[PDB]
Length: 138
Length: 137
Image (tube, rainbow over all chains, first blue to last red; front, side, top):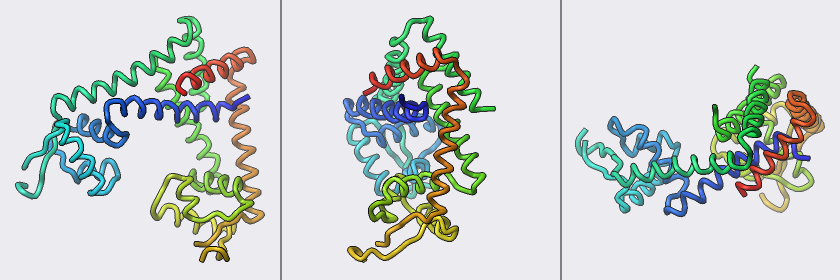
C-alpha cells in the first residue's frame, strides 16, 4: 500500500495539474496566472516589469512576453510613472475578475474533496490530519 | 477549520522540513539528497549534469555547486563519456551507503507517521487520500 509520502506528493502534484488545466480553459497559463496574482497582491504601489521579473525569478524577455500577452487581452494596462525610464502595470476590471475566478477554482476543488465524505468522516479526517501535522511540527 | 488543500500543503512542507533536518545531520542538502537518490536509481547507465538539472527542475550554479561538493566528499565521481565528449556521474561506495541510510530514514519517518493513528484510522486515511487523489486525476 502507498506510503503517506507518496500519497501527499501525488496529491500535491495533481492539485497543481488540475488547477493549471482549469486555468487553461480561460486561456491562462501557469506563469500568466502567477503574474496576474502577483499584480493583484501588489497593485497598491507602482510595479514595473523589473519588479515582476524579480518576484517571479524570470528574465526580462520572459516577463515582457507574459505582459504583452496579458495587455493584448486588456487584462492589464501599462503607463509612464522616473518618467520614460519606468512603466507601471495595473490590472483592469477583467484582470481582477480573472484573479477572482482563480480563487473560485481553488474553492471548488476544495469542495470536491469535502464532498467525498460525510460531515462526520470529514471531522475525523481533519482531526487525524491535524495530529499527523502536529507530530511533524514538534 | 483548515481546508484539505492547506493541510496537505502544510503536511508536505513539514515532511520536507523534517527530512531535510535529518539529512543535514550528514551535511546533505535537500537537493543533494534528491541528486544522490536519482543517481542511485539510474546508475546502471550514464547520467550527466544536465540529467541532474532536469530531475531537480533547477538550472544555474546550485547544480554545479551541489555536484562539486558531493565530488569533493567522494560520494560521486565524474568521468569522460567515450560516446559523448558532457561528463558522466557515478556513485562511489560511500555514496551508495548514504543513499541506503537515507532510505532507512525515510522509511522510519513513514512508520513514525503511521504510529500516530490506530490501524483502523490508518486504513481509513489511506483509503480516503487515495479516493481524493483519484478524483483529482
